[PDB]
Image (cartoon, coloured by chain):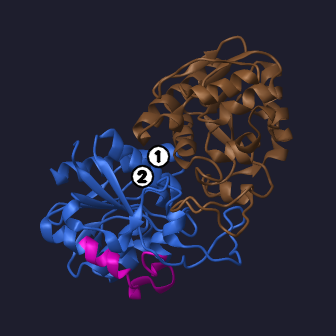
Chain colours: A brown, B blue
Amino acid sequence: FQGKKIGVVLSGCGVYDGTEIHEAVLTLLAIARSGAQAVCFAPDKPQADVINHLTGEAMAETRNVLIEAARITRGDIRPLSQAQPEELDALIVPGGFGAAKNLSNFASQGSECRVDSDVVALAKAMHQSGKPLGFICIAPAMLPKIFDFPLRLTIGTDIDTAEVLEEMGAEHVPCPVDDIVVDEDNKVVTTPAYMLAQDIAQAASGIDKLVSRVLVLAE
Amino acid sequence: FQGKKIGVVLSGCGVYDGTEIHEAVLTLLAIARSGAQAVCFAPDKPQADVINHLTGEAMAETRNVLIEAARITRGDIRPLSQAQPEELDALIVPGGFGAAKNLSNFASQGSECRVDSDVVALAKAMHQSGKPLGFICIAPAMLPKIFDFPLRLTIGTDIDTAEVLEEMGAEHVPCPVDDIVVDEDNKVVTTPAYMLAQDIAQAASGIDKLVSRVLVLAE
């Protein structure tokens, strides 16, 4: 897969107010091990909140999504507004509450949520051209808001969350932490990761499969 | 290795002002995949600085080392002052500039640096009992300040940095990104990681070997 360029969209730095750090790093690892290149992006805007990860309480400060996401990529990131679908072969979106607070407002709006316009436009551009999409953990919640047609996807086994996604037009398929769901016609791959994982090795098993599948779909 | 408890000491969240995020997550991954348990700690104190990872410039704010390190561990971390050497089988310290700013002041003091007292006491406790130590990237710079005896270690191949460590009493051994150096008598393992890595898969190759070796030394 040398030569393949995989877009990666981040939402901050940490599970509670940005991207799930394990999920993001596991994604980068799997991409690199396959010989492909990650091309990272994050929207240039303030985070919805800033959470003390030690206590779970909100902090009285403000942080920029792009600035904080740069921590994960060691500075090698660009504003999402600069993404060029023609230069990408696929798109992957890791989870964390940032996917539900910053890339969308699923966390507070549920089925009436809106998704970041630049996220919608990039994802639609991939689908137009037949380039695969990989969404992890809670990130698949954005899919039935982006695409106005039925899609096979998963967020694991949680019945309440699955009910919400169905209300939005998805077909929810149960999946364990170490496997994936694939909508073959639309080339969309999903996996639960931290929705179900009890440790990092269980999250890596599902993520590795997701990345592998995305790369196969991109050929 | 089920049952093994591996202490992990963090310094923040991000290469420039805390722990190198890739290195920390790769460490956790390798520990979990081997069936052992990571036990994470970070000192409860302010970071030396806060760096914009997008530009590399300092920011006009203050952040707590423990609070930010909790991002990497999804909240599963304790203040370093609470570490109980009797409950640990080994100790691993990932790199990032935080190891040189927060766990020590190597970044500004070089060979005249001081190391966090709780870092020194925990590391000494491991060595007393014959429990292995694994230090990654720039973290090995702390070793000849902690132990007043010669130690075989590596930070890669950088001649200037190696010269400083030698001034402090170390025996520096060249090592590539995908290998390790082991001081057998003192059970100390080091690897360069981001001192030399050009991507995350190259850092993982060295880290995986380090963790494996630490686990073997802990049996």
Residue sitting at x 62%, y 40%: A95
Q: How far from the left and from the top, in percent, is residue B113?
A: 41, 85
Q: Return the chain for callout 1.
A: B
Q: Does the residue at mark 2 contact the one at mark 1 (Cβ under 8 Å)?
A: yes
**Which quadrant holds residue A153?**
top right
The quarter of the rendered structure image containing the C terminus of chain A is top right
Residue at mark 1: B202
Q: Residue at x 73, y 66 (%)?
A: A62
Quarter of the image where one finds residue B122: bottom left
- Would you name the residue on which mark 2 appears? B177
Q: Nearer the viewer, residue A73 or A109?
A: A109
Q: Main secondary structure of the magenta part?
A: helix
What is the secondary structure assignment of the residue under circle 2?
Answer: loop
Secondary structure under the numbered disc 1 in the rendered image: helix
Residue B12 in view: no
Look at 72% across and 63% down and name the residue there.
A63
Residue B198 locus on image (x, y percent)? 54, 50
Q: Earlier in the sequence, mark 2 or mark 1?
A: 2
- The chain letter under disc 2 is B
**Residue B99: within the magenta?**
no
Image coordinates of residue B205 in percent, x first then y, are: 40, 44
- Position of residue A70 relative to residue A92, above or below, is below
Instruction: Look at the image and tell me whether residue A181 can be seen.
Output: yes
Marks 2/1: CA–CA distance: 6 Å
Task: Please state if B214 lies on the left or on the right of A72 as rendered.
Answer: left
Q: Quadrant for the N terminus of chain A, please.
A: top right
Residue drawn 23% across the image and 42% down it:
B2
Q: Is residue A24 above or below residue B123?
A: above
**First to last magenta residue range:** B102-123
